[PDB]
Amino acid sequence: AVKKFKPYTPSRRFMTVADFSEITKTEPEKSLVKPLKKTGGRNNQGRITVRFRGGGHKRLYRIIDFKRWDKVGIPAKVAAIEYDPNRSARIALLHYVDGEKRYIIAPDGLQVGQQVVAGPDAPIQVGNALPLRFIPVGTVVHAVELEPKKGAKLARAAGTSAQIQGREGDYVILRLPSGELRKVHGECYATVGAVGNADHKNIVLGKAGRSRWLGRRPHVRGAAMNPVDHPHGGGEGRAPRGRPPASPWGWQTKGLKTRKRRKPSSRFIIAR
Amino acid sequence: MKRTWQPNRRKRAKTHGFRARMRTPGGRKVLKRRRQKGRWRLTPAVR
RNA sequence: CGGUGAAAUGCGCAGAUACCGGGAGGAACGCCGAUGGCGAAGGCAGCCACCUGGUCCACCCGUGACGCUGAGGCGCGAAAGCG
RNA sequence: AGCCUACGGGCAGGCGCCGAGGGUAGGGCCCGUGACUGGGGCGAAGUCGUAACAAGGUAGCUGUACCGGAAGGUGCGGCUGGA
RNA sequence: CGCGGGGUGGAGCAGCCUGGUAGCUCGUCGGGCUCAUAACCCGAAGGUCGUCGGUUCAAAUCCGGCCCCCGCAACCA
RNA sequence: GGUAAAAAUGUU
RNA sequence: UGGUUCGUGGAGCCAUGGGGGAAUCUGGGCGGACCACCGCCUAAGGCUAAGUACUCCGGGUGACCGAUAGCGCACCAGUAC
RNA sequence: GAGCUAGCCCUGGCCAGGGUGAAGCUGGGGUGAGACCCAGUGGAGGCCCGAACCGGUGGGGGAUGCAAACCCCUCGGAUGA
RNA sequence: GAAUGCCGGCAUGAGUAACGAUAAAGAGGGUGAGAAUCCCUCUCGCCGUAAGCCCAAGGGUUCCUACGCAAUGGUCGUCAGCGUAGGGUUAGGCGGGACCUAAGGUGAAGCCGAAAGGCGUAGCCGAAGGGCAGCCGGUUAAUAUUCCGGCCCUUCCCGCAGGUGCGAUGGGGGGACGCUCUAGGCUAGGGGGACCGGAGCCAUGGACGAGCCCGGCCAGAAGCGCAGGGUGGGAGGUAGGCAAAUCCGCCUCCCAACAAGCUCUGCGUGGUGGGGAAGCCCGUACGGGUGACAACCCCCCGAAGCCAGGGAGCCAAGAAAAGCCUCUAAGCACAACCUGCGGGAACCCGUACCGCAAACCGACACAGGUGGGCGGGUGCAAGAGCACUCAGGCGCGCGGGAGAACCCUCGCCAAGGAACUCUGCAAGUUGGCCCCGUAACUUCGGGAGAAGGGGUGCUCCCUGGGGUGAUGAGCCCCGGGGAGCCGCAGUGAACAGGCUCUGGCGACUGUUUACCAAAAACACAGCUCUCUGCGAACUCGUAAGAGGAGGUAUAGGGAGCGACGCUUGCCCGGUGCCGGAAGGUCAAGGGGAGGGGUGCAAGCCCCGAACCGAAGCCCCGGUGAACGGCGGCCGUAACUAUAACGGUCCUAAGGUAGCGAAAUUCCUUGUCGGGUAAGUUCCGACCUGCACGAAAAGCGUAACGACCGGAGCGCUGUCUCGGCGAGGG
RNA sequence: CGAUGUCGGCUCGUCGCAUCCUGGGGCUGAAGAAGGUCCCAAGGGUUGGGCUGUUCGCCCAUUAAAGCGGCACGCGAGCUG
Ligand SMILES: [Mg+2]
Ligand SMILES: [Mg+2]
Ligand SMILES: [Mg+2]
Ligand SMILES: [Mg+2]
Ligand SMILES: [Mg+2]
Ligand SMILES: [Mg+2]
Ligand SMILES: [Mg+2]
Ligand SMILES: [Mg+2]
Ligand SMILES: [Mg+2]
Ligand SMILES: [Mg+2]
Ligand SMILES: [Mg+2]
Ligand SMILES: [Mg+2]
Ligand SMILES: [Mg+2]
Ligand SMILES: [Mg+2]
Ligand SMILES: [Mg+2]
Ligand SMILES: [Mg+2]
Ligand SMILES: [Mg+2]
Ligand SMILES: [Mg+2]
Ligand SMILES: [Mg+2]
Ligand SMILES: [Mg+2]
Ligand SMILES: [Mg+2]
Ligand SMILES: [Mg+2]
Ligand SMILES: [Mg+2]
Ligand SMILES: [Mg+2]
Ligand SMILES: [Mg+2]
Ligand SMILES: [Mg+2]
Ligand SMILES: [Mg+2]
Ligand SMILES: [Mg+2]
Ligand SMILES: [Mg+2]
Ligand SMILES: [Mg+2]
Ligand SMILES: [Mg+2]
Ligand SMILES: [Mg+2]
Ligand SMILES: [Mg+2]
Ligand SMILES: [Mg+2]
Ligand SMILES: [Mg+2]
Ligand SMILES: [Mg+2]
Ligand SMILES: [Mg+2]
Ligand SMILES: [Mg+2]
Ligand SMILES: [Mg+2]
Ligand SMILES: [Mg+2]
Ligand SMILES: [Mg+2]
Ligand SMILES: [Mg+2]
Ligand SMILES: [Mg+2]
Ligand SMILES: [Mg+2]
Ligand SMILES: [Mg+2]
Ligand SMILES: [Mg+2]
Ligand SMILES: [Mg+2]
Ligand SMILES: [Mg+2]
Ligand SMILES: [Mg+2]
Ligand SMILES: [Mg+2]
Ligand SMILES: [Mg+2]
Ligand SMILES: [Mg+2]
Ligand SMILES: [Mg+2]
Ligand SMILES: [Mg+2]
Ligand SMILES: [Mg+2]
Ligand SMILES: [Mg+2]
Ligand SMILES: [Mg+2]
Ligand SMILES: [Mg+2]
Ligand SMILES: [Mg+2]
Ligand SMILES: [Mg+2]
Ligand SMILES: [Mg+2]
Ligand SMILES: [Mg+2]
Ligand SMILES: [Mg+2]
Ligand SMILES: [Mg+2]
Ligand SMILES: [Mg+2]
Ligand SMILES: [Mg+2]
Ligand SMILES: [Mg+2]
Ligand SMILES: [Mg+2]
Ligand SMILES: [Mg+2]
Ligand SMILES: [Mg+2]
Ligand SMILES: [Mg+2]
Ligand SMILES: [Mg+2]
Ligand SMILES: [Mg+2]
Ligand SMILES: [Mg+2]
Ligand SMILES: [Mg+2]
Ligand SMILES: [Mg+2]
Ligand SMILES: [Mg+2]
Ligand SMILES: [Mg+2]
Ligand SMILES: [Mg+2]
Ligand SMILES: [Mg+2]
Ligand SMILES: [Mg+2]
Ligand SMILES: [Mg+2]
Ligand SMILES: [Mg+2]
Ligand SMILES: [Mg+2]
Ligand SMILES: [Mg+2]
Ligand SMILES: [Mg+2]
Ligand SMILES: [Mg+2]
Ligand SMILES: [Mg+2]
Ligand SMILES: [Mg+2]
Ligand SMILES: [Mg+2]
Ligand SMILES: [Mg+2]
Ligand SMILES: [Mg+2]
Ligand SMILES: [Mg+2]
Ligand SMILES: [Mg+2]
Ligand SMILES: [Mg+2]
Ligand SMILES: [Mg+2]
Ligand SMILES: [Mg+2]
Ligand SMILES: [Mg+2]
Ligand SMILES: [Mg+2]
Ligand SMILES: [Mg+2]
Ligand SMILES: [Mg+2]
Ligand SMILES: [Mg+2]
Ligand SMILES: [Mg+2]
Ligand SMILES: [Mg+2]
Ligand SMILES: [Mg+2]
Ligand SMILES: [Mg+2]
Ligand SMILES: [Mg+2]
Ligand SMILES: [Mg+2]
Ligand SMILES: [Mg+2]
Ligand SMILES: [Mg+2]
Ligand SMILES: [Mg+2]
Ligand SMILES: [Mg+2]
Ligand SMILES: [Mg+2]
Ligand SMILES: [Mg+2]
Ligand SMILES: [Mg+2]
Ligand SMILES: [Mg+2]
Ligand SMILES: [Mg+2]
Ligand SMILES: [Mg+2]
Ligand SMILES: [Mg+2]
Ligand SMILES: [Mg+2]
Ligand SMILES: [Mg+2]
Ligand SMILES: [Mg+2]
Ligand SMILES: [Mg+2]
Ligand SMILES: [Mg+2]
Ligand SMILES: [Mg+2]
Ligand SMILES: [Mg+2]
Ligand SMILES: [Mg+2]
Ligand SMILES: [Mg+2]
Ligand SMILES: [Mg+2]
Ligand SMILES: [Mg+2]
Ligand SMILES: [Mg+2]
Ligand SMILES: [Mg+2]
Ligand SMILES: [Mg+2]
Ligand SMILES: [Mg+2]
Ligand SMILES: [Mg+2]
Ligand SMILES: [Mg+2]
Ligand SMILES: [Mg+2]
Ligand SMILES: [Mg+2]
Ligand SMILES: [Mg+2]
Ligand SMILES: [Mg+2]
Ligand SMILES: [Mg+2]
Ligand SMILES: [Mg+2]
Ligand SMILES: [Mg+2]
Ligand SMILES: [Mg+2]
Ligand SMILES: [Mg+2]
Ligand SMILES: [Mg+2]
Ligand SMILES: [Mg+2]
Ligand SMILES: [Mg+2]
Ligand SMILES: [Mg+2]
Ligand SMILES: [Mg+2]
Ligand SMILES: [Mg+2]
Ligand SMILES: [Mg+2]
Ligand SMILES: [Mg+2]
Ligand SMILES: [Mg+2]
Ligand SMILES: [Mg+2]
Ligand SMILES: [Mg+2]
Ligand SMILES: [Mg+2]
Ligand SMILES: [Mg+2]
Ligand SMILES: [Mg+2]
Ligand SMILES: [Mg+2]
Ligand SMILES: [Mg+2]
Ligand SMILES: [Mg+2]
Ligand SMILES: [Mg+2]
Ligand SMILES: [Mg+2]
Ligand SMILES: [Mg+2]
Ligand SMILES: [Mg+2]
Ligand SMILES: [Mg+2]
Ligand SMILES: [Mg+2]
Ligand SMILES: [Mg+2]
Ligand SMILES: [Mg+2]
Ligand SMILES: [Mg+2]
Ligand SMILES: [Mg+2]
Ligand SMILES: [Mg+2]
Ligand SMILES: [Mg+2]
Ligand SMILES: [Mg+2]
Ligand SMILES: [Mg+2]
Ligand SMILES: [Mg+2]
Ligand SMILES: [Mg+2]
Ligand SMILES: [Mg+2]
Ligand SMILES: [Mg+2]
Ligand SMILES: [Mg+2]
Ligand SMILES: [Mg+2]
Ligand SMILES: [Mg+2]
Ligand SMILES: [Mg+2]
Ligand SMILES: [Mg+2]
Ligand SMILES: [Mg+2]
Ligand SMILES: [Mg+2]
Ligand SMILES: [Mg+2]
Ligand SMILES: [Mg+2]
Ligand SMILES: [Mg+2]
Ligand SMILES: [Mg+2]
Ligand SMILES: [Mg+2]
Ligand SMILES: [Mg+2]
Ligand SMILES: [Mg+2]
Ligand SMILES: [Mg+2]
Ligand SMILES: [Mg+2]
Ligand SMILES: [Mg+2]
Ligand SMILES: [Mg+2]
Ligand SMILES: [Mg+2]
Ligand SMILES: [Mg+2]
Ligand SMILES: [Mg+2]
Ligand SMILES: [Mg+2]
Ligand SMILES: [Mg+2]
Ligand SMILES: [Mg+2]
Ligand SMILES: [Mg+2]
Ligand SMILES: [Mg+2]
Ligand SMILES: [Mg+2]
Ligand SMILES: [Mg+2]
Ligand SMILES: [Mg+2]
Ligand SMILES: [Mg+2]
Ligand SMILES: [Mg+2]
Ligand SMILES: [Mg+2]
Ligand SMILES: [Mg+2]
Ligand SMILES: [Mg+2]
Ligand SMILES: [Mg+2]
Ligand SMILES: [Mg+2]
Ligand SMILES: [Mg+2]
């Protein structure tokens, strides 16, 4: 339900803002186990490591329950759907009957005022968490743990979802958003349904400044440099790469695989 | 235009002060050379 | 092995074709099935449910000439094609 | 500040509005022309190929898309003006 | 003027390094097939190897000198 | 019938 | 691999980082690969004066200088700047 | 040595005054319901004119200078990267 | 005797350039050994969103006064920011600390590193941020929110008096937050006045007049008053807020739904306290008195400041901890805490002065640079703009003459208007507001201030809305119509677009070579390829660790291309990358056929071939929005000419679309066509493309540009071709 | 080479003659006018524009003519760039 703008200035005819109608009437945030101070920083102790980060708007870190075995069997009421600037996806405020207040990452189709519960019992309705060994084969799922009791680490960007393809012993087979088939242990929790805000792919930032609002400083091509700075640099005007294409550090960047070959996780991976 | 020397008591005493010399082994050798030479002021005079 | 009028390219001793067992995935629905049916046309074919339109018959009950066509307009509109 | 015949008047004159037209500027319509370029038509009996008419030697036609010196070829769906 | 490669039957190309014998495709000529042509089939002819010299028993072949052809180079102020 | 295929040209 | 005059050389000896891994006098190391004979030492624990080096400081001396020299400074100098 | 400069992190501050009038609300119109069309309201924008502020386009001056980058006229941005 | 030698001294240029903004000086009188330069008075000029006041940083005696002029002052100097000496900075309330936390720093635990050291949770440090209690006047030569005066507060600590279960660094609430536009009511500030209070003044033709001139305030407890900000009250039940809670949270029916009520600010009013002009008289550099028993009133404008944590909209989603309120834990309930009064106690540092500058940063009394607040009036539509001017501060620390060339900064010009020239470079023209009117093209926004026009001053009359006042006067903001007056000219001065046509490149705003390049370069949204399944890939680091990220394929990294539109053809032969449990080759190692050295021999020590031995390479495939590449020679058609067609050789494949003498074309000023009187440039074409071409992208494209080229109109000292005048030299 | 700043333009010139014109003359296939060619002659004169950075050159409109060369392809302590 993406917002379009009229071309009243340039860079608004293309500019595009997401729809906030799923955001219910909760524009400010909850507190005390809800935003911590978020440390802005482009760099480690000292030097820059991820180049071209900086600037951007100030943010507060909405602390999310990624490990929802804490409240097995305890139901919840969906009180709010909020904006998280730290994520592509939306967040859902839950009040527990137990009394706690936590954010789960808000799935698609989840509406306000809905009972939602985690555990092995946990009927297969959107938002509920279960082990993977209890979820039926073929259902789309998200917020998937990789190894059990370690936290939800898979399928949690906007609109992403993973799908169960089968079971094999203590492990189940998941089709990831990458298309990779992965053996994930059955005791790993996973929240059913896709993540939603699936129109996040269709946004157009419109102008250069909107990338600066996100903390994305401008990205300098290597061909516009000097050979001290980059392999592609140098040359009287516009050299055509002169070599197989490479990073500033020399490693090639067109097809060169760099997964560690002898990784012990490789015997749980079936596809690309 | 704007020249190089723009003074600050805070900056001068935290960069060139005695306690900043005694943190590093480099600044500890600085004062050692200044004791040995006979300097009247081991550190820049800050008030 | 494929393939043809005949061949060749191709696939194949790095273990193919042919066979069994398991898994994924998409598209189209055999027999019923036709000179059949439905729809205003384009067109519609496995099955289930929901939501929905047109139409045919009988009873001759009610309104009572409300009708027919239709320049524009509006809507539908195979396949190919475009985002 | 003039002239008068019946003068708290008239004439000449003066000011003003509209005003033919001329000037400046910008649009609209039409005609002639224009290096070059597209395709159309008729011409001397030219060159290259065989598309269509017989199952025209790949049934033909068709809308569209792509390609090819050229007719045309092929894909998708439709037609009997074919079996 | 510099460096490199080239000239061979009518057309286009081999053969030159490692001297002894010139081959391929199209074309031309003669004969078939056709009513006639093209296509196709069977035969056949054709080359002072750009020239001028010298090396050798012997030169398309090796070496030089000229005549043409193709490509590169012709910079610094 | 729901059921298979063969290589140019000809002045007016 | 380092140390020794020894740069892989016939390369021992002395230390070692890695792997294997003993023996207690009929035990063990060395005498420049190695083997035999003849000899010298007794590792894998530690301490140990003196002779030796230096001159911030004190003294003596000079075929050392004499204010552009001799220390950067004979003078309130590691100062002013 | 980041008291100049380049980038970023934390925390404060600054941007006179005019224009243009997007979305959206309200009302009318339209329809079977819509889309949509008018008005009024509304005040969006790396929007427009232009001071402070940040710059440094063209020319002249300056050239042992006022100045080891200056001065005058002119010019770009000026709610945003 | 030389080394552009070193150090020092003194010459030359030379009484030459210069004396540091062209804001500006003149006279009288003092003082003095000595005055353009010091003091005083009068006149003149300059700033006045400052060149005037108040803070912060920095500076550190420069402040005040007395005595002085050797040097410092670009001259002089009796003066001074200078020399000698003396004086001067007064705080519970301002600022900082005995309070808190941010980035970051440090760091018991813990991890790491040859050593030195590097990380690192809690904690601690860390400030223009949060918190917190003083306003107005008067005094000194020099200090005051600091001393004094009046009014008002905050902490502690000890007492009695009355209340309550008190009680932690622990739990919870709160603190607590964006940007932009804004409502209502006040305040700051300002304007006007027939009203009130004033020394005085009628000048030169006129005026004794509601005349001129000056001034009509400030703070202020409780108490009210007006605006406004915050917040629901019970009852149970309760597993969560890492022990406990009556608190918070979550459910559940009851009553409120309002700011009714509690509080909390702001602004008025308030016991009372203070200030109080012009002008005149004086004795000082600086002030003092009178004016005055001062008056101390009414309207209007009105904020960007206050009520503040107000409201609305939007996406980019907008600090932390303490103080504060409450809750319970040990412990304690003779304690303790809350409220009211009384007495006592209230420490350390800074306080002078300069502060857009002669006291800071620039070697200088340097035309430079430097953060926050106040910054009045009138007119110009508005305004912090521009011109003049209050308060206040200055005339820039060499002057006097002259009136050449020449230079700088200005002004004007006959006739011509770009003939100047690399180029209209420069300078002119245009210029603000109101009203008409406005093209191709287009992404429907634009282009648009298109272009091109008209009006603009002053007086008189009539008349329509508002705001504050009560519905009225007045005061203020906006209008309409009519009639006249003057001048060469009415945004009468100052501030204030020249315009159009057409191409090249880049889409656009933006960024860059501080100090010769602001551009077509970089960036940019957007497109594609590729890597990355999370202890991710990548980066920094020996490591630990950290970034990525407190992210998870709609995410992160790398590379190119660079909005958008239509598109992005063929070659996997070589290079790269990807995929291949075959085979060839291949190191240490395993292996020992066999041989050697010594021993009397057991033995001890060397070499050592088959064979088993990874990655890598060879090999087989794939892959272009991966590195890259995309042919030659002949002949041929009803006139030549050309070649749709053919032959042949080679390649991995032989440049398709679209453009093309172009930012690309050597020959070249190619050849036609247009603009011109005349066009090596420009535009439209042809294609013979030396040497375009599809993501080092191809062809286009509205809007946009201090980019680059061509043309035209307007206007002009650019020129013909100069001349005159001004000011600083 | 411990520095001799280079094309072109502007400004200012000066010099040479093998002369573009004007002046004098011989020959002419010189009727006349207008030319051709050669000899004497430098005293003076030798235009304004379009294109290009141009020197040169080609055009436009004229003229008595639209001369060639030297002076560091004269001249940057004179200027432009
Ligand atoms: Mg809390
Ligand atoms: Mg750190
Ligand atoms: Mg550090
Ligand atoms: Mg880039
Ligand atoms: Mg570069
Ligand atoms: Mg570097
Ligand atoms: Mg490199
Ligand atoms: Mg190039
Ligand atoms: Mg390169
Ligand atoms: Mg600092
Ligand atoms: Mg009936
Ligand atoms: Mg259709
Ligand atoms: Mg379709
Ligand atoms: Mg599609
Ligand atoms: Mg009468
Ligand atoms: Mg056919
Ligand atoms: Mg046919
Ligand atoms: Mg056919
Ligand atoms: Mg085809
Ligand atoms: Mg078909
Ligand atoms: Mg049939
Ligand atoms: Mg050949
Ligand atoms: Mg040959
Ligand atoms: Mg024959
Ligand atoms: Mg024949
Ligand atoms: Mg060179
Ligand atoms: Mg070179
Ligand atoms: Mg060159
Ligand atoms: Mg034919
Ligand atoms: Mg060694
Ligand atoms: Mg050794
Ligand atoms: Mg050696
Ligand atoms: Mg050795
Ligand atoms: Mg060892
Ligand atoms: Mg040993
Ligand atoms: Mg040994
Ligand atoms: Mg030995
Ligand atoms: Mg031995
Ligand atoms: Mg021996
Ligand atoms: Mg021994
Ligand atoms: Mg021992
Ligand atoms: Mg010794
Ligand atoms: Mg001594
Ligand atoms: Mg000395
Ligand atoms: Mg002496
Ligand atoms: Mg000395
Ligand atoms: Mg900095
Ligand atoms: Mg300001
Ligand atoms: Mg505005
Ligand atoms: Mg509207
Ligand atoms: Mg606005
Ligand atoms: Mg703007
Ligand atoms: Mg602009
Ligand atoms: Mg502007
Ligand atoms: Mg600045
Ligand atoms: Mg800059
Ligand atoms: Mg400038
Ligand atoms: Mg300049
Ligand atoms: Mg200035
Ligand atoms: Mg502008
Ligand atoms: Mg000497
Ligand atoms: Mg000297
Ligand atoms: Mg002298
Ligand atoms: Mg003199
Ligand atoms: Mg003099
Ligand atoms: Mg002189
Ligand atoms: Mg002189
Ligand atoms: Mg002088
Ligand atoms: Mg001076
Ligand atoms: Mg001066
Ligand atoms: Mg006297
Ligand atoms: Mg003035
Ligand atoms: Mg301070
Ligand atoms: Mg200070
Ligand atoms: Mg100083
Ligand atoms: Mg002093
Ligand atoms: Mg004195
Ligand atoms: Mg003096
Ligand atoms: Mg003295
Ligand atoms: Mg003096
Ligand atoms: Mg005196
Ligand atoms: Mg003083
Ligand atoms: Mg003094
Ligand atoms: Mg204390
Ligand atoms: Mg104390
Ligand atoms: Mg503090
Ligand atoms: Mg503290
Ligand atoms: Mg602290
Ligand atoms: Mg820390
Ligand atoms: Mg240690
Ligand atoms: Mg540390
Ligand atoms: Mg503070
Ligand atoms: Mg504070
Ligand atoms: Mg305070
Ligand atoms: Mg004072
Ligand atoms: Mg005071
Ligand atoms: Mg007091
Ligand atoms: Mg209590
Ligand atoms: Mg707390
Ligand atoms: Mg007041
Ligand atoms: Mg007032
Ligand atoms: Mg009175
Ligand atoms: Mg009089
Ligand atoms: Mg008043
Ligand atoms: Mg309640
Ligand atoms: Mg509890
Ligand atoms: Mg209310
Ligand atoms: Mg009051
Ligand atoms: Mg009060
Ligand atoms: Mg008084
Ligand atoms: Mg006075
Ligand atoms: Mg609010
Ligand atoms: Mg907090
Ligand atoms: Mg704390
Ligand atoms: Mg509270
Ligand atoms: Mg003070
Ligand atoms: Mg003070
Ligand atoms: Mg200031
Ligand atoms: Mg300086
Ligand atoms: Mg001076
Ligand atoms: Mg100074
Ligand atoms: Mg000074
Ligand atoms: Mg001065
Ligand atoms: Mg100054
Ligand atoms: Mg400033
Ligand atoms: Mg004001
Ligand atoms: Mg003003
Ligand atoms: Mg005004
Ligand atoms: Mg006026
Ligand atoms: Mg104005
Ligand atoms: Mg203001
Ligand atoms: Mg001003
Ligand atoms: Mg004054
Ligand atoms: Mg005049
Ligand atoms: Mg004139
Ligand atoms: Mg005139
Ligand atoms: Mg004109
Ligand atoms: Mg011209
Ligand atoms: Mg000219
Ligand atoms: Mg031009
Ligand atoms: Mg100009
Ligand atoms: Mg004018
Ligand atoms: Mg245009
Ligand atoms: Mg418009
Ligand atoms: Mg206009
Ligand atoms: Mg235009
Ligand atoms: Mg007037
Ligand atoms: Mg009012
Ligand atoms: Mg009212
Ligand atoms: Mg008029
Ligand atoms: Mg103006
Ligand atoms: Mg232009
Ligand atoms: Mg061009
Ligand atoms: Mg641009
Ligand atoms: Mg620069
Ligand atoms: Mg430089
Ligand atoms: Mg520049
Ligand atoms: Mg620019
Ligand atoms: Mg694109
Ligand atoms: Mg690091
Ligand atoms: Mg590393
Ligand atoms: Mg990490
Ligand atoms: Mg993170
Ligand atoms: Mg990615
Ligand atoms: Mg990326
Ligand atoms: Mg580019
Ligand atoms: Mg278009
Ligand atoms: Mg291949
Ligand atoms: Mg290839
Ligand atoms: Mg390849
Ligand atoms: Mg491979
Ligand atoms: Mg071996
Ligand atoms: Mg071996
Ligand atoms: Mg062995
Ligand atoms: Mg291998
Ligand atoms: Mg391509
Ligand atoms: Mg012919
Ligand atoms: Mg061919
Ligand atoms: Mg092709
Ligand atoms: Mg041309
Ligand atoms: Mg032409
Ligand atoms: Mg022409
Ligand atoms: Mg052209
Ligand atoms: Mg062409
Ligand atoms: Mg080219
Ligand atoms: Mg290109
Ligand atoms: Mg190319
Ligand atoms: Mg490409
Ligand atoms: Mg491009
Ligand atoms: Mg183009
Ligand atoms: Mg383009
Ligand atoms: Mg364009
Ligand atoms: Mg520009
Ligand atoms: Mg720009
Ligand atoms: Mg022209
Ligand atoms: Mg002039
Ligand atoms: Mg003059
Ligand atoms: Mg003058
Ligand atoms: Mg030289
Ligand atoms: Mg020399
Ligand atoms: Mg010399
Ligand atoms: Mg002569
Ligand atoms: Mg003559
Ligand atoms: Mg003659
Ligand atoms: Mg004659
Ligand atoms: Mg004659
Ligand atoms: Mg030109
Ligand atoms: Mg030349
Ligand atoms: Mg000459
Ligand atoms: Mg020459
Ligand atoms: Mg020259
Ligand atoms: Mg020069
Ligand atoms: Mg020159
Ligand atoms: Mg010269
Ligand atoms: Mg010279
Ligand atoms: Mg140049
Ligand atoms: Mg230039």
Image (cartoon, coloured by chain):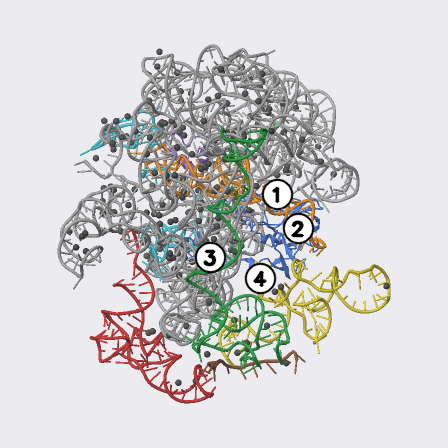
Chain colours: A blue, B purple, C yellow, D green, E red, F brown, G cyan, H orange
Subunit bearing disc 4: A
Q: In this view, does D47 lie above or below A168?
A: below
Q: What residue type is labelled 2?
A: Trp
Q: With A182 as the anchor, is H55 left or right in this view?
A: left
Q: Name the residue under label 4.
A: A270
Q: Name the residue under label 3.
A: A252
Local secondary structure at mark 3: loop
Question: Residue B46 location, x and y as percent?
Answer: 44, 30
Dot 3 crowding, Cα within 10 Å, few <14, some 14–19, many 20+: some
Which quadrant would the C terminus of chain A be assigned to in this image?
bottom right
Q: What amino acid is at disc 1?
A: Pro
Picture quadrant where residue E64 is located: bottom left
N-term mark: 1 or 4: 1
| Residue D24 in the image: above or below residue E47 | above
Which is more toward the observer, C81 or E71?
A: C81
Q: Is tag 4's residue or tag 2's residue first in the polypeptide sequence?
A: 2
The answer to whether residue F11 is above or below residue A217 is below
Q: How far apart are marks 2 and 1 (CA)?
A: 22 Å
In the shown orientation, is residue A102 left or right of residue D55? Answer: right
Rendering quadrant holding ligand 142: top left
Q: Which of E72 and D28 is in front in this view?
A: D28
User: Can residue A33 be seen by looking at this rendering?
Assistant: no
Q: Please identify the quarter of the rendering in which residue A265 is found.
A: bottom right
Q: Which of marks 1 and 4 is in front?
A: 1
Task: Let me know if marks 2 and 1 both belong to one chain.
Answer: yes
User: For mark 1, what is the residue?
Assistant: A35
Mark 3 and mark 2: span between their CA atoms? Answer: 43 Å
Whether residue A69 appears in this view of the structure is yes
Label located before the other in sequence (1 or 3): 1
Query: Residue tagged by mark 2?
Result: A69
- Provide the chain ID for the residue under circle 3: A
Residue G4 percent location from the top left of the image: 33, 50
